[PDB]
Length: 143
Length: 143
Ligand SMILES: Nc1ncnc2c1ncn2[C@@H]1O[C@H](COP(=O)(O)O)[C@@H](O)[C@H]1O
Ligand SMILES: Nc1ncnc2c1ncn2[C@@H]1O[C@H](COP(=O)(O)O)[C@@H](O)[C@H]1O
Image (cartoon, rainbow over all chains, first blue to last red; front, side):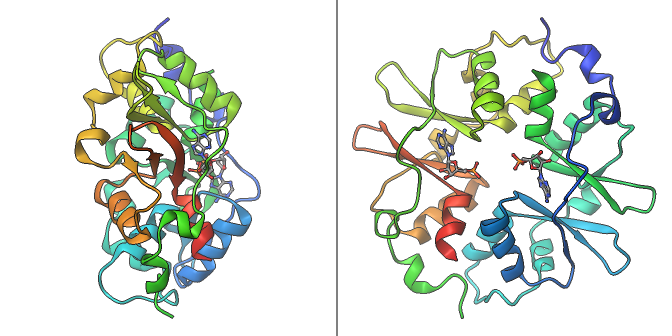
């Protein structure tokens, strides 16, 4: 009773039916942090894909990013774009932002662990949002 | 419209009424990972204080810790204690595990950001659990 079972690890996200693929809440690179703050508190989601003018995912903005902004010693207000979080980290260029439905659970779990991130955005061939896979999604499938 | 407002940052957790102080789900240092996995999926909480034989908090076990276990290349099963997560990180010795009600939001936010952790356990003078403060708790108060 290996954990995880090898047969699970070799299956794809699509095969295991892992992730959320409807009603995804997301923002734009030009969205102010106040908009994200309001979504997090009132809509109750943990992270928001951030898309460019073409609809392509370039970041994911999380509750922790807001707290990190709050801790900055320099003066900020909430009118700053969510892209200021990119000064702290680049999920995009580290290859720990996106995934595809055909990737295996082994690949997804290793990518999450590589950068200690808690979700990935599932995208299409144009880097447009199809869904989100979070640690909760993976745990549900493991049981 | 500084973010966060300085008057918020100077107030304590108790003053701002931030955190969960009832119905805290928690485990022991001798608890197997399978028990934690079942709590995470069925009880739907994000992290679990881990307490020793005296009831004192010595770690906090999170969904990410399970995923980190899953990614280990060595052979594991779920009968291993939750304390195996301590091979990867020590929240305790880094001083990023616990907090007190009288600490300021500035102190709490800086401690969360220091180690990039998403919650702290609120404890008493004996390191026994009183509650949990997570990023969601802090955001609710910021709005
Ligand atoms: N931006 C989002 N929009 C919709 N669902 C989301 C979003 N972020 C996470 N989820 C889903 O919310 C559930 C809980 O995720 P987690 O908050 O990370 O515990 C999972 O099924 C995620 O796939
Ligand atoms: N082990 C736990 N038992 C009870 N409440 C918890 C626990 N962990 C987190 N919470 C609370 O669950 C809510 C959502 O936290 P978060 O999952 O981190 O978004 C917050 O009000 C936390 O204080």
